[PDB]
View: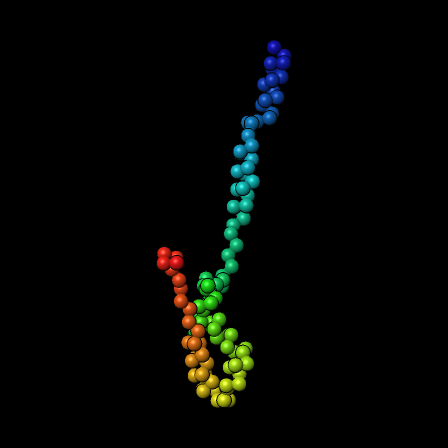
Amino acid sequence: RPMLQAALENLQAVGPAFDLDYDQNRAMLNTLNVGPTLDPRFQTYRYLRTPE
Amino acid sequence: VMQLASWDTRREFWLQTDYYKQRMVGNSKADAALLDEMINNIQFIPGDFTRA
């Protein structure tokens, strides 16, 4: 009887058990919440014959 | 190969050679006509691996 009551109390105060895969996703989600950094005015070509 | 056939590369080469500098008469319009003639004096012919 008594330690069985103890088991209920201990598991109640700990909560659900999580694996490693859960923790990795949370760390990745933090970076995604920051958001991308946008810098305009970057070239999208290069010259092989400049106009003259 | 890309730099060999480039119109830009041929233009920078002639401007730093003594062969071209002694042929400048001093008129801005004449020199530009002379320089454009020299650019066409270099020809690049791509090859074929099928015919070796």
